Structure formats: structure tokens, C-alpha cells
Image 1 (cartoon, rainbow, N blue to C red):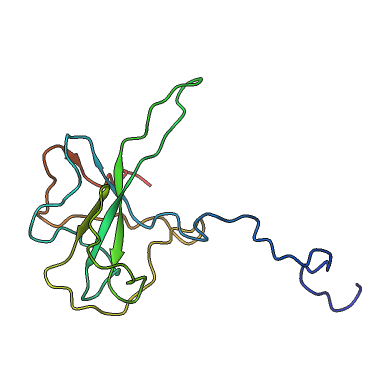
Image 2 (image 1 turned 135 degrees about the horizontal axis):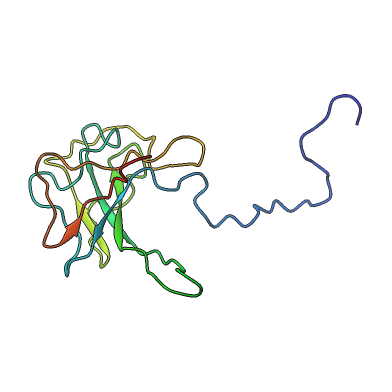
Amino acid sequence: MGSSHHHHHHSSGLVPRGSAMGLPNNTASWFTALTQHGKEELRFPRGQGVPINTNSGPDDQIGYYRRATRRVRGGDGKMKELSPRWYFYYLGTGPEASLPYGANKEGIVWVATEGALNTPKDHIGTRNPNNNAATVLQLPQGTTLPKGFYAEGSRGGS
């Protein structure tokens, strides 16, 4: 004490203890999710498949969407059940780029750009409450939605 103060090192608990993280360190969701209400699953039409994106893949605009199902306790003990939606998961090389690139699944919809070249560029998908909101995808002119699907959302008004 007095002069030269060291970090928070009481020197009582040797054990590291990461406050039981088990959650996204600093990544919430730097993007939106296509809410599917129809009777089908996500699967953007031909042409591109994946939104315009921002910088989650220079020459490797590939990836997939993970069907996210959130629940909300409406009223006093009610269940509204948040509108089902799939969150975008950019993919290329710089970032994870570990997956098999097209690992077909049940609640997962894979999609690759018109010929992924594979390039370095990782620095997204981390909407840490302090950095910035989510760029939220924006399908090009076409790339419409399947049977009865609702675009990412894009809340009109930040």
C-alpha cells in the first residue's frame, strides 16, 4: 500500500476462477437473423444466398445461419415465444474457418458465395455492449425470401 499499487491480487485464492463464463466473452451478435414464420426452413434463393455483408469475407463470402430460438416471459407468467430466426454466421479463412465448410445439419442452413476464393479478414460477429450495434445483413436487389419468410428485421429506428 501507499506507493506502487499492484493489480487486484489479494493473494488469497490461488485458483484462477473465470467467474464461470460459459458465455460469449465479448460477442453478442454483430448482425441480424432472418425470422422464418412460414412452414419451411431458411435457405436464401439462388444467385448469392448470403447477404451483402460488410467485411466478413473479402473473397470468401461463405457461411451459414444457426436457427436461434429465444423465449420471452410475456405478461405475468405468459409465454410469447420470440419469433424464430436464424442468425448469420460469416465464414472464410481469417476467422474460425475450422468447420468443414458446408457442415449440413438439422437447424443449420449452409450457403457459399459464387466461388469462394478464401482470404484473410477477421474482425466481426462481436457486438460487445460498448463497441457498436449490429451491421445487420441486407440482401441485395434480389435474394428474396422462400415461401413465407421475414427478412433479418432491420428495426426501423436505432
